[PDB]
């Protein structure tokens, strides 16, 4: 079986400069999760590859960009914080993050936070560069907001600001989770420590001068 996580997303610019509003397209994601055998705090090493594809600012991303991630979360009243650092290389659509729970044991499975913990590092092929909303909003950045519905379980609501602070791309997130089952796959820690490949469907939202996205994450179950 799989634990479905239905993602609804919207992104809006932080600044006032012109942004690219894209035609409908996908970001194709492949991810891999690792454990650092020498890291003794609860943590996740996350490696993502992200590439734009058809349905059928950019100057800041020519090289390797350091990343900082900060998340404050509260799921069924369990409060936690996650802090991470990494590097992204949009030329290859590649990012690497090491993320630590700084408040102790993470109260949810790490895979459920993968999507929350920087689509500006996607590799857009040359024919598609005019559809890269994410880089066009930089350096001032964008707000990424999501609701994530876990089938037969609770939901996450997230709000993140993704923007350059000096030379560093920062992803600062607040996450609130409610209505989770104490016995379920999430609070009961019944998800495999791995990740499947997914396509993120992106469409423009002219009223909010931004984009929206819809996709379904499939978490493998493991006890």
Image (spheres, grey):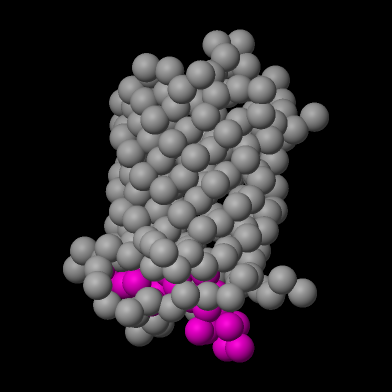
Residue 207's quadrant in the figure? Answer: bottom left
Q: Position of residue 69 (x, y in %)?
A: 34, 49
**Who is closer to the viewer here, 23 or 39?**
23
Q: How many marks?
A: 0
Q: Is residue 87 visible?
A: no
> In the image, is residue 188 above or below residue 50?
above
Q: Position of residue 135 (x, y in %)?
A: 40, 74
Q: Which quadrant is the N terminus positioned in?
A: top right
Residue at (55% x, 11% y) in the render: 182
Q: Residue furthest left?
A: 166
Q: Residue furthest bottom?
A: 127
Residue 80's quadrant in the figure? Answer: top left
Q: Residue furthest front?
A: 207
Residue 23's quadrant in the figure? Answer: bottom right
Q: Residue furthest right?
A: 1
Which range is magenta? 120-140
Residue at (45% x, 68% y) in the render: 206
> In the image, is residue 69 above or below residue 29?
above
207 to the left or right of 28: left
Magenta-span inclusion, residue 69: no
Residue at (52% x, 84% y) in the render: 129
**Who is closer to the viewer here, 6 or 164?**
6
Q: Which quadrant is the C terminus positioned in?
A: top right
Q: Position of residue 95 (x, y in %)?
A: 48, 62
Residue at (63% x, 70% y) in the render: 25
35 to the left or right of 99: right
> In the image, is residue 184 above or below residue 61?
above
> In the image, is residue 93 above or below residue 151?
below
Q: Is residue 6 visible?
A: yes
Q: Position of residue 71 (x, y in %)?
A: 33, 40
Magenta-span inclusion, residue 123: yes
């Amino acid at each position: 079986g799989v634990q479905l996580a239905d993602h609804y997303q919207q992104n809006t610019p932080i600044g006032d400069g012109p942004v690219l509003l894209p035609d409908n397209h996908y970001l194709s994601y492949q991810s891999k999760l690792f454990k650092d055998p020498n890291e003794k705090r609860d943590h996740m090493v996350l490696l993502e590859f992200l590439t734009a594809a058809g349905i059928t600012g950019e100057e800041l991303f020519t090289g390797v960009v350091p990343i900082l991630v900060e998340l404050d979360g509260d799921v069924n009243g369990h409060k936690f914080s996650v802090s991470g650092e990494g590097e992204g290389d949009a030329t290859y659509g590649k990012l690497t993050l090491k993320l630590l729970c700084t408040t102790g044991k993470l109260p949810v499975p790490w895979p459920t936070l993968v999507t929350t913990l920087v689509q500006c590092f996607a590799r857009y092929p040359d024919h598609m560069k005019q559809h890269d909303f994410f880089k066009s909003a930089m350096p001032e950045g964008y707000v990424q907001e999501r609701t994530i519905f876990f089938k037969d379980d609770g939901n996450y609501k997230t709000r993140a600001e993704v923007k350059f602070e000096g030379d560093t791309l920062v992803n600062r997130i607040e996450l609130k989770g409610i209505d989770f089952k104490e016995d379920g796959n999430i609070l009961g820690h019944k998800l495999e420590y791995n990740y499947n490949s997914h396509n993120v469907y992106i469409t423009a939202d002219k009223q909010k001068n931004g984009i929206k996205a819809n996709f379904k994450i499939r978490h493998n179950i493991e006890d």
